[PDB]
Image (tube, coloured by chain):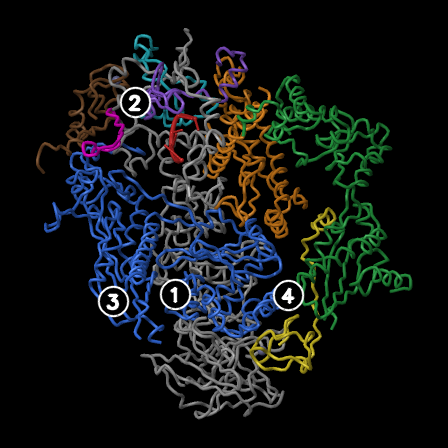
Amino acid sequence: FSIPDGFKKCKHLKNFPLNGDNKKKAKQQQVWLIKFPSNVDISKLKSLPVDFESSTTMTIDKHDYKIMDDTDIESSLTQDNLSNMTLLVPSESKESLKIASTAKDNAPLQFDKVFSVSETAKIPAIDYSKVRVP
Amino acid sequence: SSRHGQKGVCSRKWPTIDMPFSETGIQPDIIINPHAFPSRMTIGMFVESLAGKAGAL
Amino acid sequence: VRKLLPESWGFLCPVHTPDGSPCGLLNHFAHKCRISTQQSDVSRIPSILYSLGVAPASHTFAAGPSLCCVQIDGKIIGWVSHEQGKIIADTLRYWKVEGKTPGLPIDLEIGYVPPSTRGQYPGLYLFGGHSRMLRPVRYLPLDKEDIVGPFEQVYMNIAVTPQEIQNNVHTHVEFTPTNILSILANLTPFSDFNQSPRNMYQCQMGKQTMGTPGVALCHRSDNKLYRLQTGQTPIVKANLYDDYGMDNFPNGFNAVVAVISYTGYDMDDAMIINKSADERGFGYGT
Amino acid sequence: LRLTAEGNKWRTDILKTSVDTGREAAAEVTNLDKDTPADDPELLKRLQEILRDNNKSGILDAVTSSKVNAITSQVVSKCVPDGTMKKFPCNSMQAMALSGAKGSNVNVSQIMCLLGQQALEGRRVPVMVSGKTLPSFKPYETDAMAGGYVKGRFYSGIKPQEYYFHCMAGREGLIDTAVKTSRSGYLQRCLTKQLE
Amino acid sequence: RTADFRTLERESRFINPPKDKSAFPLLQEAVQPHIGSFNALTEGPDGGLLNLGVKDIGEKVIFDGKPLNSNSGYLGNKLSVSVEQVSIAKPMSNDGVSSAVERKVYPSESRQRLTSYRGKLLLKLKWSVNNGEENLFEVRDCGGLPVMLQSNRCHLNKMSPYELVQHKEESDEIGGYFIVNGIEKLIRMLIVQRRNHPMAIIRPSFANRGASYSHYGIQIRSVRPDQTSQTNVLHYLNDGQVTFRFSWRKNEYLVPVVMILKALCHTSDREIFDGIIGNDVKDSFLTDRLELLLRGFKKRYPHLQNRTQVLQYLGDKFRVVFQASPDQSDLEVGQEVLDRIVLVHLGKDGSQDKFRMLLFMIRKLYSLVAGECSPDNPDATQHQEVLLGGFLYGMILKEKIDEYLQNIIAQVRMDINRGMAINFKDKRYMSRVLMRVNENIGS
Amino acid sequence: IVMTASAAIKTPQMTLPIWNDVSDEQADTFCKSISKVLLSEVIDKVIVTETTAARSYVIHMRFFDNNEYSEEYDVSKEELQNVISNQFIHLLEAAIVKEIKKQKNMNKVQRDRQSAIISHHRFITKYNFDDESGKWCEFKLELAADTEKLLMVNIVEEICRKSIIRQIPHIDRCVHPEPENGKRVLVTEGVNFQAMWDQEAFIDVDGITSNDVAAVLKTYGVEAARNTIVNEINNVFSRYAISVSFRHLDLIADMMTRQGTYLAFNRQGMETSTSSFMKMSYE
Amino acid sequence: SEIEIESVQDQPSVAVGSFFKGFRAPSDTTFDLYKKKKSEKDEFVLHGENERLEYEGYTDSSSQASNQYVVGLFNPEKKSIQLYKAPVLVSKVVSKSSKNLRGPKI
Amino acid sequence: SVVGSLIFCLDCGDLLENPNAVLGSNVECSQCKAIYPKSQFSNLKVVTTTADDAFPSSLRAKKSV
Amino acid sequence: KAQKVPIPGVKQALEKKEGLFRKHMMGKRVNYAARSVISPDPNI
Amino acid sequence: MIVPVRCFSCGKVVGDKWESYLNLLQEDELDEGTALSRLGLKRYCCRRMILTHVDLIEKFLRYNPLEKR
Amino acid sequence: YQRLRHMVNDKFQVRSTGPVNSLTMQPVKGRKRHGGIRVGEMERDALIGHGTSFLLQ
RNA sequence: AUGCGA
Ligand SMILES: [Zn+2]
Ligand SMILES: [Zn+2]
């Protein structure tokens, strides 16, 4: 197939070190998802205040932003696999993507943390004392 | 009608001598009866009278 | 249907309504109202929304009154928290009054519907398309003009004058409370001092009034024209009398009036004119 | 048409009392404690309860109406010819209403005192689904005026928010006036045919 | 000093009217909402609204019963006729015949003559033969279209006050109205449902549709780019069944909503459920109504296993009426229906987005059914927009050109049903058919 | 009245004079004691747990307090037993059958009740009742897989508003408005003389009145309907405080009674008149 | 208290796909990755097949062009994320039954 | 998948025919081929409730404030 | 009773609504009649 | 249309005071009140006659069909 | 003050004789047509009220 | 018929 000539086959993929520091139910490793407007260049970052859990204020080229964090839908603490946020894992440049798992349980896994970059705005208050003149 | 939606027909063309004359030496163009105002509450007309008079003087 | 609703504030005149059968059916626009005839910048609005934290509708994969829906012209583009609903509504209005968001025309109408117990179904329905009714109000945070439509107006706190602006409440203020009146209602002097239905009969008189139809009457051929030759400019007028130029086509004249029952032919609906005054040409019409 | 400085003094002083009346009735019909803050969250939820109920909202209108109309009655009974700038055997407006040439004491008080509480189809002002009777009113404004009680008078004018309500009453009057005569023709002809 | 007389200023303006800009910009700006409406039929994106309208009328196909002796029932040679552009010219008058040079026609003339103020309406006709075997262009004159005064098509559109005086007009003539047979007529502005947005309504007509109807329903008035409208209503039956209502040839039609869902995009039942309730997994009310809806459709149409079959079923079931049989398959007729009915404000290929919006309409409808949301008010100015007279002008134009092509097709049908005397190729036939229908839609 | 003489008034009322000896508190007691009580009207909460091979509907109806509805509507839990076991269940079971056509603790005395109601009703399987107050009513309903689907909440609701604890046929409510300008009375929102006839120990029957002309004619005869028309219309003008000579109204009534009935003034009533042209000139 | 980022991986490797609630796929189903190089940007399309159906996924271009997704893998013990660019693809799977049709007419 | 009283085909997401009515071991999809009445038996139950609307009353009114 | 706004027959004649009997029999135009705007006068 | 000959209410000839009054607002750069005071319109009947005038004839006159344009 | 175009003064009409419709031979309609005002049903009934049966005929 | 005095 490899349709719409405007497409190319893949030639370069990367192994996933799932277990180089994994231990079965012993390493509390995590995978996080953050949504980034195309306007930001993630590669020009250095650290990520995702660790604030809630206080995810964020500074992108000295510009202040706030990072909305969600805790449901795909990561819901409610149903067994309440998320379709499917992970597609590769292996090698000569292999097709794989369903994420943590053992051979037919288990689609989930992102431990989901983050979202939200554009902040000054929205300065009205100077009431100047405007509400009698 | 005035600018107040208080419309009325001219019942008669009163002779100028028979009109009432002010000590200013004038007799009005139009006479409207006062009892029309109490139901209509056309008080905008009262102020229009006092303002148009001021503004002419 | 004839019931006068509060939604029309700023859009339709509460007094420009015929009296009779048509009453309530034939509304009249406010003298400060505009009508959308185009649509714009819909193309950049998704981009900025994505910047503001809107989850793409393919990716959100969740839906309900429990969540805020961002839609543009009936194109649902994303979902956010209701809190982000309010954050977006306010920051968006800020970029609208600003000049920094070219994908954001001043005249976009931002329908915020907050969550409400059995209230209006929540959402942020933006509209930019044609035929929208739009009216100016003054946005206080930028002390600059802002265009509001009837949808968003319901939930907006617009103080009527600056001294009545209540703290932490009114985000806009009327430019002038006349902005809520139609043309004829502003044309009536001190119309705010008379019983409303007498003001509406005033609209019916000025609308049914014999006046100056034009000056090209030597080049028209109407089945009827009424042209008052002895025309004057009211001494008492709204400043919109000049701003709308009704002085071009004066429809009446300033007369000496005595408010007096005296002659006995002045009752109820009958008024007397000076005979010599008519002989001097008073109200002469053709 | 003018009052004395005294008559405007009583008028203004009595008109100072409606500010409590608005919410006091709002918490009575809501059946909530006295002086309950105009910003109590439970008050707002209960008031949304009334907003969503046509019957409860109707009772809220009627009770607020009885109280503010009691304030009107107070105002007129106090200020009356007791405060007019010139009295009877001179005050022509009083002459016409009292003689019954034209007018009623209602008209004279509406010029000299206040318009008072507007009503529609038998009850106070419509409310938007946002809980607001005018853009300028926050949802659930407990002011009587925000319910439509107009303190302004024709001699001193009406606030614009107040003109929108007297315009409401004036329209609903013109509608009822224009349909009521069409509802009496068939009553006439239908039985006039029989008793002829 | 508050409303002072402009006395010297006025008398100067009477004596020496402006040669550059009318005063009273509010005066010209007040009827501006009309003029803009009329100009959008001649200028705007691509060429103005009217060219979008002709982009929406699409094609009108007719087959000569191409005999050929599939070549004997698979096309008596396709002939698809459409309209590329539509041109409007400012009023001109040629003297006597036409072999004369035309003159710009002025409104003063229409009034003094007490006649209409007409502009020749022209439209670039595309005559496509055998899907491309032959292309024919024709600039057709469609009679005199009454032009709005001071429009982007009236000579007074750009006249300075002084010029206006030079043309015997009120130095401030607002225009926006029409001189037809000398009588000034305007199109009344109308209050219509706010376009493109689902309005939750309880209406006793909804129960009046028949048995199992509730009061509840959704009404969205989808408006196409060209501003032509198509109203879509959703009705909740007492049985939990949801039906999708629309209107075609001013006849009403009901289809199960689950059919239009499987029709927009191929998806699983789990995808529609996931589309509606989402994280809201707790509405036994909604869970159960949706099991009734989906399971009930699965009961009725167990053989509609895929979206394509559905498309064949819809095109097949209305192909008799959408006038696209002698050429299209039930898949094509079905898809053209989808594109022509369902949230047409979203446009062609918005079919997944149209799907998502439709899911939003189902969710809102159940929010009304349970009562978790308030009902809206069609009659609140909040929920209303304004159909401008000029826009009606454009809709009616679109309808008139669609019908005019319908008349062409009727003429071909009669000729092929009474003679088959002439091939789709003959220029005689193009001129002859054109010469046999009357086409001055201006009248 | 005049134009259509409709035998179905929009606001049918029957006025009841209460004896001088009838206390105001006894009178309010009687007002509560006569008004209809629907089964829905006492219901607090309904939880349906449909568990499916037999399609099981475990309906747990958690009611109000026994004393609460007993003090608002003067009814008991035992009355609820009889109504449920006889009325509610039988009617719901019939509605379930209608839905099929549309498709196509636990003591021995309690066990005997459940078994008896099952024996009277084909759908029910278990019956647990809050005999300690009446706070709830749990009964197990088992249905064949072939039962597919119903909206049991909606079915229950519909049967709930159709069951009555106390119903006077055609009579809805007896209220105790304040007496004014006349004897103490109770104004009912319905018309049923025969039912008030049994209440004679509180109501001077000779003084019963109503707004329903037709009901008067059927019960008390032509002169009572005659006086009812002239009084009711006179009340219509009295509301607007208009004076109208009684001679006019009484004449009009006599014309409506010219045949001894409630002969309206439309074409239907005109038909019986003798002038064919007079008919011709109407409709 | 914020977690630092140690290293970033910027080139295509892992992808994410939104599906129906219940997606599980064969124990071995394989996912063909594609790439598009449009001027200065790649649009991605995924294609796979299974024993009955075939699953094909694509990017929501109007959100794709206006929003860009980043993935990282964090270790609590190493304080380090391996970042992966992943396209989110809303994929639908058609079966052989979804490949049957009638004549083009009756 | 089974949800509430809906059970979707695990392979195709189709709400496959209810195990309670199958004439067999399990079930099978009309879009997919997954086995129903033989695999997960489900124990279909729903806690359905009243909408807190069918029953207006004076007692509800004293219970509503 | 036929099978569009057709010409009316005799039944849609003097009957129905206003018609002849109502509009030209039970009420008619009359000669020796005038219509005018009324004006007050205390001296008559 | 044209400055009235006489003040309807009073009777004072007023048609003579137009051009000078307009000149006096031009030439004398006066104010309407003082201009009318120098013109002698010492009654509001005579004050209003000229104050309210709108000599619209200048607008009519540009439509004269008896000269080419 | 403004003069309304409705000089209903001009609306006066009198007819002591005029045209009649051939299908009735009854006064035609309209002031400009010298038509005759209608004595409608209500005026007929009302005249019967007065007892003026010789006036009604 | 529509609008109109109303
Ligand atoms: Zn399946
Ligand atoms: Zn003078």
Is the residue indicated by label 1 positioned so its CB lies within 8 Å of ligand 1?
no
**Same chain check for tags 4 and 1:** yes
Residue at image location 20% in from the left, 40% down from the top = E110
Residue D18 sits above or below residue J15 on the image:
below
Q: Quadrant of residue E173?
A: top left
**Palette colour of chain J:** brown
Mark number displayed over residue E288:
4
Marks 4 and 2 sit apart, C-alpha to C-alpha, by 82 Å
Point out residue F117 in the picture as x, y percentages from the top left corner: 84, 60
In the rendered image, residue I2 lying in the magenta stretch gets the answer no
Specify the farthest residue to the top: I43
In the rendered image, residue C226 lying in the magenta stretch gets the answer yes
Marks 2 and 1 sit apart, C-alpha to C-alpha, by 80 Å
**Palette colour of chain E:** blue
Marks 3 and 4 sit apart, C-alpha to C-alpha, by 61 Å
Q: In the rendered structure, which disc, 3 or 1, sits on the residue that comes first in sequence?
A: 1
Marks 3 and 1 sit apart, C-alpha to C-alpha, by 21 Å
Q: Secondary structure at mark 2?
A: loop
**Palette colour of chain H:** yellow
What segment carries the magenta color? C212-231
**Palette colour of chain K:** purple
Mark number displayed over residue E324:
1
**Palette colour of chain F:** green
Q: Chain of mark 4?
A: E
Q: Nearer the viewer, mark 4 or mark 1?
A: 1
Look at label 2 and name its amino acid: Leu
Marks 3 and 2 sit apart, C-alpha to C-alpha, by 88 Å
Look at label 4 and name its amino acid: Asp
**Palette colour of chain D:** orange
Q: Chain of mark 2?
A: B
Q: Nearer the viewer, mark 3 or mark 1?
A: 3
